[PDB]
Amino acid sequence: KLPPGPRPLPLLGNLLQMDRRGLLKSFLRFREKYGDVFTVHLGPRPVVMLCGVEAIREALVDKAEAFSGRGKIAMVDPFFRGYGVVFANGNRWKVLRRFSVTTMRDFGMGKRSVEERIQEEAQCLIEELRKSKGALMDPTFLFQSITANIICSIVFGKRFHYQDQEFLKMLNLFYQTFSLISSVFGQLFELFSGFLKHFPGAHRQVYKNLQEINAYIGHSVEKHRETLDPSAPRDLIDTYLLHMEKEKSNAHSEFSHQNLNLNTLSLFFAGTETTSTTLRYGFLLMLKYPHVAERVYREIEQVIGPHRPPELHDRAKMPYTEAVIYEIQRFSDLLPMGVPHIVTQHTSFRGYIIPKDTEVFLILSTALHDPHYFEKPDAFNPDHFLDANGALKKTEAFIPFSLGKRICLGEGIARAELFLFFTTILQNFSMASPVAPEDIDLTPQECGVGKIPPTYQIRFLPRH
Ligand code: HEM
Ligand SMILES: OC[C@H]1O[C@H](O[C@H]2[C@H](O)[C@@H](O)[C@H](OCCCCCC3CCCCC3)O[C@@H]2CO)[C@H](O)[C@@H](O)[C@@H]1O
Ligand SMILES: CC1(C)[C@@H]2CC=C(CBr)[C@H]1C2
Image 1 (cartoon, helix red, strand yellow):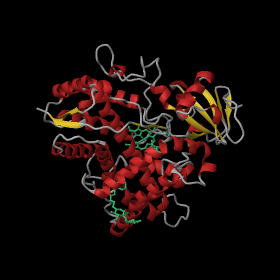
Image 2 (cartoon, helix red, strand yellow):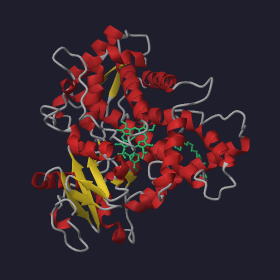
Image 3 (cartoon, helix red, strand yellow):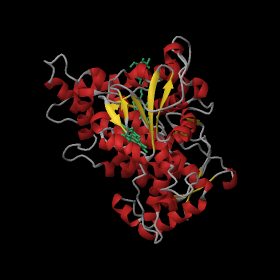
Image 4 (cartoon, helix red, strand yellow):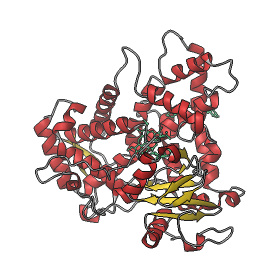
C-alpha cells in the first residue's frame, strides 16, 4: 500500500487539509502526524513525501535504481515537455546528462578553467561596484549577471556586459519567471493545472517569458551552425552541433534541435537563478548580521590580504568563510522540496509499495533544518558548521543540491561561484543599508518550488 496520509476527496485531493501558507507548510503539518514518509494527493496525483536525511538518502542513494526519475513542475512542463537534461527521463536523460556533465567540465586545450572564468568575472564585478560610487541598489541584476556570465562563457564562448539592456531584459525574464513559478498561484497550479490551464494566469506569462529567452538561444544556434569549424569547436553549442552531425542519419537521435534549445535554456535557468538567489540571501544575511561579515573580512585579511585575488586553493585555509557560505545555503534553503522525482519501477520502501510512475518529493528543507544536526536550525548561525576549535565541521544533513543520480550537476561550479564571488566582494567592500540590522526581515517574498528573498537595497562601500 502507499504510505499513509490524509484522506482525500475526489477531484480536490487533499485540498481542504492544506495550509494556506503553501505547499511546504502543508507538508510539514502532515509530517507532524504521519512521520517522515507519507502520501499527499495534489489534485489528481498521489505524491509520496520523503522527509529527513535518513529517508531521502535511503531513496536517492540506496535505491537509485528506482528513485532516479524526474517528476513534473506544472508551471513549466508545458514549455519544456520533457526536453533538456533537467526535465528528461529515460535514455534521453542518460545521453543529455552525460553530454552536459562532460561539456560543463571540459572545455578544450587552451581554454580557461571554471576557476579562471569566475575570477575574471569577479574582477569585472569589482570594477562595476567601484564605479557604482557607493550608491544604493537592489543587487539582483548583478548577482544574476555574474552567474549567467559563467554559463554564457561555457555555452556561447562570450560574456555579456552589465550595461547591455538586452542582456538585462533576459535576466529580468529569469527573475520574474522563478518568482511566478514559486507564487501561491504557481503552487495552486501544481494541484489543479488540468482545470486552471483553460484560463488566464501566471502559467501563460511563464510560457511567454521562457519562449522569449529561447528565441535568443535558437538564433545563436543558427549563427553557430553557419560559422562552425568542425576542427575547432568554440563552445558547448559547437560541440553539440558536431554530435548532431555525427548522428544525423538516425531520425531518433537525442541530439535534436529541441533538446539543444531546451537543454541550453535549462542550463541557464538552473545556473543563473539558483546561485544568484543564494547570493541575494547571503548579502541580506550580512546586512542583518554584520559581525559575521566583519569576521569573514578579518579572515580574508589574514589569509588572502587586501590585494591578491581570492583563489579556490584559499578555501581550506578559510574555515570561517566556508562555514558562513554553508550556513547561507542551509538557511536560504533554495529549493525546499527539491525538484520532483518519479519512481522508475515498482519499489518497496520501508514496508510500503510505491508503484512505478508515482511522483516523489524529497523535502530537502527537512534535512537542512534537522535539529539533531543543527542546534536551533531556524536561526542563522555559522557555528552550525564549526567545531569547538573553529575548524570546518561538514555534515551529511547538508544536502542543498540533493543526492544520487540526479544530484545537481552544477554543484562544483556553484560552490566555486559562491566562494570566489563572496570573498572577492567582501575583500574589496563593506556593506551598508538604510535598515538597521534589528529591523531587517528575512521572510521570503515567495516560498514554493523556490524560496526567494525579499527585495532590498544595499551599498557597497570601498574599503580603506
Ligand atoms: C546554489 C546553487 C544551486 C543549488 C542549491 C542547486 C540545487 C539543485 C537541486 C536541489 C537540484 C535537483 C536535484 C534532484 O533532482 O534531486 C538541481 C538540479 C540541477 N541543477 Fe543545480 N543548483 C545550484 C546551482 C546550479 C548551477 C550553477 C548549475 C549549472 C552550472 C546547475 C544545474 C543543474 C542541472 C542541469 C540540474 C538537473 C540535474 C538532472 O536532472 O540530472 N545548478 N540543482
Ligand atoms: O528571434 C525571434 C525574436 O528575434 C528578435 O529578438 C531579439 C532581440 O533583437 C535582440 O536584442 C536579442 O538580444 C538578447 C541578447 C542577450 C541574450 C542573453 C542570454 C543570457 C543567457 C540565456 C539566453 C539569453 O535577442 C532576441 C532574440 O534573438 C525580436 O526582437 C523578437 O521579436 C523575435 O521574436
Ligand atoms: C529553478 C530550479 C531550482 C533550477 C532551474 C530550474 C528549475 C525548474 Br524551473 C529548478 C532547477
